[PDB]
Image (tube, coloured by chain):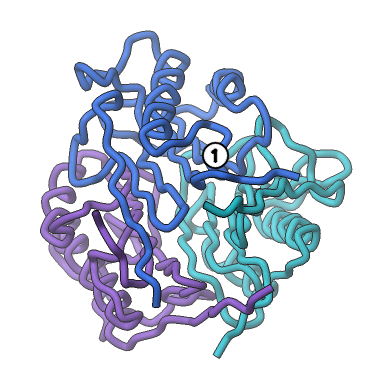
Chain colours: A blue, B cyan, C purple
Amino acid sequence: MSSLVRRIISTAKAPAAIGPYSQAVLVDRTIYISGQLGMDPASGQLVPGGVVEEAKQALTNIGEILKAAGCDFTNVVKATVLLADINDFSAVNDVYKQYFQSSFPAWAAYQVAALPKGGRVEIEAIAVQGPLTTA
Amino acid sequence: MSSLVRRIISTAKAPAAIGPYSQAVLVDRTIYISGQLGMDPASGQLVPGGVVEEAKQALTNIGEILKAAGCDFTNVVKATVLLADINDFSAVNDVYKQYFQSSFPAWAAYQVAALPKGGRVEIEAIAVQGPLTTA
Amino acid sequence: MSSLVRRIISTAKAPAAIGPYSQAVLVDRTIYISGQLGMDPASGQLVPGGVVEEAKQALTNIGEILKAAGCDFTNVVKATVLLADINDFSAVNDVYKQYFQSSFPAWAAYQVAALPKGGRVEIEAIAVQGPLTTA
């Protein structure tokens, strides 16, 4: 069979790994992006201000990883939004909507028991490397 | 590179979006289906009767989304079953089994802290558009 | 369109199914592996010793499923690590690192409310059937 391209995506514009994972893996045309917390890329510390600020930073981090792979938010096809508190659903929704301005991904959003570093939100994503033709 | 097909799947036979997501995204041949709660498509209210009734409605909803994409349950390759209570595992298993009557998908099933709308179960799925040849 | 290969992966070297799922599904070149607990393949009982021993057994189980599909850990592109306790993150990380000795997968790791069988850890994975060419 054909040898499919598998590339580790890595950018200093997103946080360093806090463990045994890659920021994202591109395989064939699919990009699996690791769960992102609202961590500042330079410090690796959660940004202050709680879930809204954290959600913004997490999505900014995903954006930088997408850019490293020659993609943007239009390439995302599935997202998972993990919350520390289900009462934050509406607030996070309003943040998320600002990044996906068409062809909204499939998703799931729900509350887990706890995230690393005491994070209030973690977002995972799957993207597909372009070009994509959307009818 | 080739421009891959990316299509938003949308049917009025499944619940309207309660937020910034598509019911499903078809990209190349893979269909990412959003997490479905046991919501009535017409009202958008959770069906009464608790987890068993909700599980049935959620799977019915996935079925309608699959149909919109020219697929059925035989096309599902991976499911995720999110529970509000791990004690409901056996009950949900018995519901789920009635929809997948061969070539059972890969899966994960476990308890989360909370689902949207106070749901007792949420099911996500990945399918692949046919034809599929199963040896 | 072409008829894509869909194959159920099954090995007696990994635990029997405790419900309506396949150990893994290969579709085209992507392998979706079901969530694995730290269950002994012969008995179907969780191994003693808590999360570290369970994590080792779960990863051993994934390894046997990969082998059945003609793959190994180098083929894994995304993992999900579900914990019963976020305080176990560092311990599980140290176990996991021993299995992935290059080209680390994308991942997400976090605490859920409860796993089947009172498990302390469950690991899901996505792999891509080789050959893969890593630059």
Residue lying at the far bottom of the rendered structure = B135
Q: Chain of mark 1?
A: A
Where is residue C41? Give x, y as percent.
27, 81
* Residue A48 position by quadrant: top left
Quadrant including the N terminus of chain C: bottom right
Mark 1 nearby-residue class (10 Å; few <14, some 14–19, many ≥20)? many
Residue at the front extreme, as displayed: B1
Q: Position of residue B23 (x, y in %)?
A: 70, 45
Question: Looking at the rendering, in which quadrant would you find the C terminus of chain C?
Answer: bottom left
Vertical arrangement, residue B91 with respect to residue A88, above or below: below
Q: Is residue B59 visible?
A: yes
Q: Is residue B121 left or right of residue C64?
A: right
Q: What secondary structure is found at the residue carrying circle 1? A: helix
Q: Residue at 71% x, 49% y: name it.
A: B7
Q: How many numbered markers are drawn?
A: 1
Amino acid beneath label 1: Asn
From what the image shows, is residue A10 above or below residue C128? Answer: above
Residue C86 % position (x, y): 26, 40
Judge from the rendering whether residue B69 lies leftward or rightward of residue C41; answer left or right.
right
- Please name the residue that numbered disc 1 is placed on: A75
- Residue at (15, 42) in percent of width and height: C90
Asked whether B67 or A113 is in front, the reply is B67
Q: Is residue A7 left or right of residue B33?
A: left
Please indicate, yes or no, whether residue C44 appears anywhere in the rendered image. Answer: no
Percent of width and height locating residue B86: 47, 55
Residue at 61 percent of width and 40 percent of height: A105
Question: Can you tell which quarter of the image residue A56 is in?
Answer: top left
Q: Determine the residue positioned at 31% across, 41% down.
A: A9
Q: Is residue C55 left or right of residue B107?
A: left
Q: Nearer the viewer, residue C60 or B58?
A: C60
